[PDB]
Every structure is written in structure tokens, then in C-alpha cells.
Image (tube, each protein chain N blue to C red):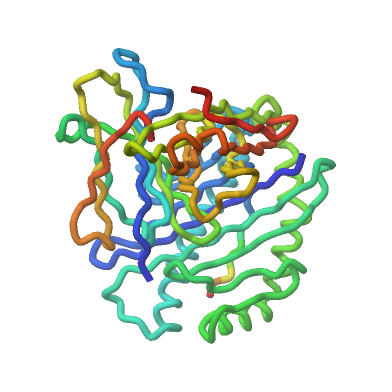
Length: 276
Length: 9
Length: 99
């Protein structure tokens, strides 16, 4: 179906401990495929998925050069942000960026992104029009003015509508074995008595790809949103993900509860019950 | 693939 | 501002005593990015634990997976110990093969 490519930059200052560290990771959907760390012994863009190893040396050189220039760029960005926020050079600060494109089943651009953060807060973001900016505050408005004058949005848009979708289409083809395979969750419900009159029903989803999933408990067909313990979807470390949802239920009422599972890998949503 | 956005803040 | 890590300790595959597996500690939702994460076997630090490349969610909060090969047994206790600027003391979360 639809697919995404995203690059994630983290630039972290560390006064007294060297120049700011710059890290990039690239994903297609929920699959990491490339990394860069300025603290590496000989920093370069490195493959993290088999299907990207196909790319010739020129790709790796070009990609490495971008990241190496970014290390210097984001060091300047950090220095600039200190001035814009009247901050001292004693503190550690973080700039983040996430950019990329979403394509439809036909590979056409659905939408592009380019968002920046400072110390975990929105700073500036390219609007969906790929022509204009939303600045979060008066400091980011200064960047906005510079970027407007420098036609940054036009360069972003050229990338988002061109290379971003073109390279993502190629990655999807090269990695079709995996990037175009959904793995459905393996599911079950466990039962643990809490006390004589309360029991925990826990609905498990394991081994699924991609990470998007919905797990919900209903009591008598009514969603138990407020009473469900839902953990964050978590990486198993073999590309797949795990999640569970739990409710505490009155003893003897277990059968009034149903677990509902939606996942792209499932032909239809699943209903599970405690199977004593 | 990335592209180089070289304009600073 | 600062955000405290969410912590989950779990295995890659369902735990089966005497069967090799992976012990994972997933830390998420935290900011800033500096974090200290140890995997413990019977209260002692496991050597040579690996971790994922630093990345973050749409809300800018960071996440990392720390992991080591391990063979669960009946007797052996496992845990994750996490420190972060938001924590006045390191947090220990015990592994529970049902969580």
C-alpha cells in the first residue's frame, strides 16, 4: 500500500566535551536502512538493511558527504540557536530534524515533510504546501525570514517531489521481499488472578510488521479505553514488533470481555477471548 | 537518498 | 524541557528455560537524549550489551533498544537499570516473562 521514507537528524551540543555530536538515521516505513554518527571512528553513511547494500560506492560517497557537511551545518545551527534564545554556552542543547516523503500504492507523492525542533520543542516546519513555513516562536521567525529569502522551501519541494519519491520507489523495489511484506501479529489472551475477585486479562500481539496496530478490549461490546493498560509498541529486535493491552476484570466476568486486533497483515480484524 | 540543505538558521 | 523514559524489559521470543533468546530493554519517550541503560543478571551488569542507533518519535522524544543474548533459566533473575537526568535515582525494572 502506502510507504514512507524519513531521515532523522539529532545534533547535540556538549560543552567541555568536544564539538556537537551529529547522528542521522534513515527509515523506509519501520525499517532502519542507513546510519551516520559523527563520533564514529571514520564517520560515514553505513548500510543497516540488506537491500541498501546494492547501492554503488558513488551513492555511499555522496551520502557520506551530505552527512559530513551536515555535521558542520548543525554545529552552526546550534551556535545560532544559542544567540536567538539568549542562552549561555554552558548548557547542552539539541536540534532535531525529521524530513521525507510519503508515497501511495502507485508511488505518487502523497505528502512531503521537513520539521525541525530545538530542545524537543517545535522550531520550524515546512507546511504541507511545500512552499511556506510555520515558525513556533520569534526565534524561528528569524530563520523563516532567512529561509524565505534563500528559497529553502523551493529546494525542499524539488527534493520531495523528485529524488525523495524516486529513491524510495527504488528502495521499495530492491527491498520488496521485506518492505512490501506485512507480517500479521501472533495473538493470545492470558489470564492472571489478581485476588479472589479480580483477574488480569492480557491480550498479546507478537511478531508483527509494520508497527502500526490497534489492540482494544471491549466489555459487553463497549470499548474499555479508560480502563485498559496499553503498553507502547516495542521492537523485538528481529524487525518485528510487540504490544499488549490489559484489563482487570471481575472474577466470573471474563467471558464478557473481547480483545480486538487490527493490523494491515490481517485480512480482517480479529476478536479474541480468554480461552480457559 | 538525502539532499544537502546547506542553509543555516 | 525534560521528559522521563518509559521502560520495558522483555524477551525477543517467548521465554523457554535453557533456550537462548534476547533480553531487550526498550527506553522511549525521553528527552534529552543522554541515557544510561544496563542489563543486569542476578543484580550484576551484563557486559557488552548492544543498542540501536539514536532515533525519535513524531513528538521529538527519543527511543533506544538495548539488547543482549541470554538463556533464561528457572533461577536466574534479569532486570534493566535506567538513569536519566529526569531521575534522581536509577530505576530498576525486573524482567517478567509475562510482561
